[PDB]
Image (cartoon, rainbow, N blue to C red; front, side, top):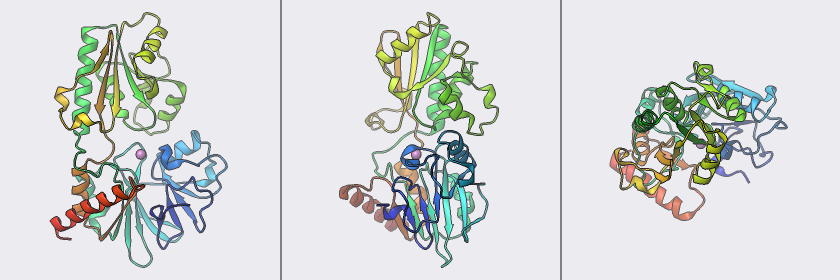
Length: 341
Ligand code: NI
């Protein structure tokens, strides 16, 4: 059954709850963003109102084939009424189209559900500055102090220089970027841009990117592999045998692959800076794992929560075991006592 942390008290609203069949008493299904753990269960046959960003709407319509009459896109940063209840959608700094949702309850409670987010100080000067928030439904993916990672800007800087140098040293080297979902487009876009190329990809991935209101996108991507020296591939295929394979298919147009695996956290975050990264090499094929996160570090999360000073926090990630739950509750208490709310 749909868990309590997917229900918004005193509404008939649910968030990211599509895989439980009809939820008894739900009048409106919110979707924070187009990732499959969140949309799981959506399809052309769903016949209940879905509320979401314009971008997420474009993806429901063109990739899942949900019928237009059920998609209610809302602009961001705009006070809107949904079945008699004031709501605001805010940028979640996660993947394209991803949102946080502010709920103003008829009783006077204000609730924020973060969906998936990467907390940023820029959120402190949005519509959230303007009033008190009583309840926080929090993306707790990296709620533990070992989880450090660099800024997105640091990581992109590294990837750009790495690729530019390898391609200038050898003009017959190919760049491959792994992907399996929306998000992290800046990786392959910044690389392509420094090398004077469009990015090449399959037809299914091209369709997905054409939904995302990226400015000047027709100038940046293509379905023509031959014409492009940055290739996107399924993340599954980013390994030595699967690259070699791919390298055969290019027909002697390239002799070397330089490949990037945009991971989240991996344990060498605890010992190594971005400046001192190295790849796995098997011949002319090299694979960088780069820690580009679209989830809050432990410190970024801490800061956002200490600024907000919510009265109650309800975790939406890592809730399945009593030990995770217990550990999270301890950090929330430390934060509260340190900050005096
Ligand atoms: Ni996500």
